[PDB]
Image 1: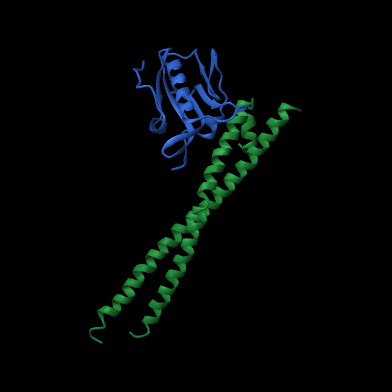
Image 2: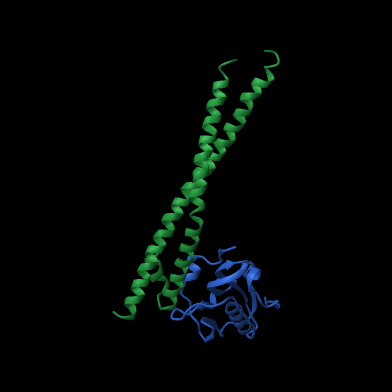
Length: 129
Length: 127
C-alpha cells in the first residue's frame, strides 16, 4: 500500500485514457461513415442537377415548365447537405489531435506500468482484455 | 508534421518477456535491455514513436523481435526520470544494434524506424 498504490492509481488512469480513446474512436468512426454517406449523396445530387438543366438546354432551342422548381429544390438541398457535410468534416478534423494524443499517452502509461512491474495480465485487466 | 507511428500492437507492447543473460545499459533516460543469450537469428526492431518536423520526437517503446516473435531486446524511457531527445533514441538504437550484433545476430530496423532514426547497414543471416 505504498509504491503499489501508485502502480494501481496509474493503472486506473490507463483505464480512463483507454476508455476515452475507444469512446472518441467510436465517435470518429460514426463521423467518417456519415461523411462518405453524404458526399456520395452530394455526388448524385450533382449529376442529377446536371441532367435537370441539361433537359432545359436541350429543349429550349425548340421552345416541361414545372421542372425548374425541381432543379431549384435540388440545388437547395445540395448546398444544404454540403453545409452539414462540411460541419461533419469540421467535427472529425477536430478529433484527429484528440485521438493521437490519447493514443500516445495511453501507450506511455502502458510502458510506464510495464516498467514498474505490471505484467501483461495486469495490463489487460485495465485494458478490458 | 506531428504524427504518431506504431509498429507494435498492444499485445506486443504489453507482452511479458524473460531474459536469460540480462544486459541493461542506460542512454540518457532511456533503458536499453537485451538478452545476451540470443545468437544467430534475424532480429527486427519495432517501435512506437511520435514524429515532428519529419524527425523522430519521442520514443514510446522499442522492442527487438525474432522471426518467431520472441522479444529479446527493448529500449524504453525510464519511468522515474524525465524525457529524452531525438539524439538519445539514436544512441540507444546504436547500443542495442552493436550489442545484439556482437552475438552474431542479424539485426534489422523497421521501415518507419529507417525513415527517421536508423543505424546498422546489416550483415548476413544464418539458416
